[PDB]
Image (cartoon, rainbow, N blue to C red; front, side, top):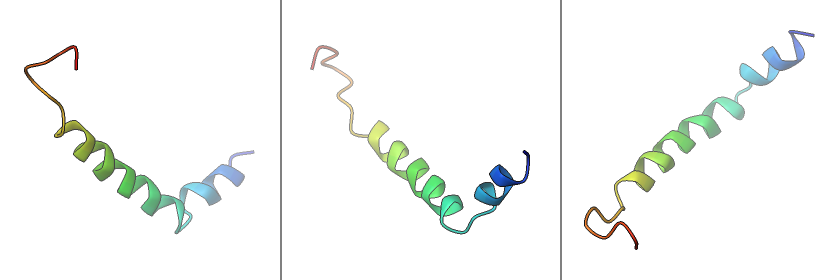
Length: 39
């Protein structure tokens, strides 16, 4: 079925969790050590 997953895609709770996960992953990229690769 292509409506059960559509309901989750257009869900109010799911479209904001994916938005906050993008910012969390973006912040996780800016806390890396550029010098010490074996850190």
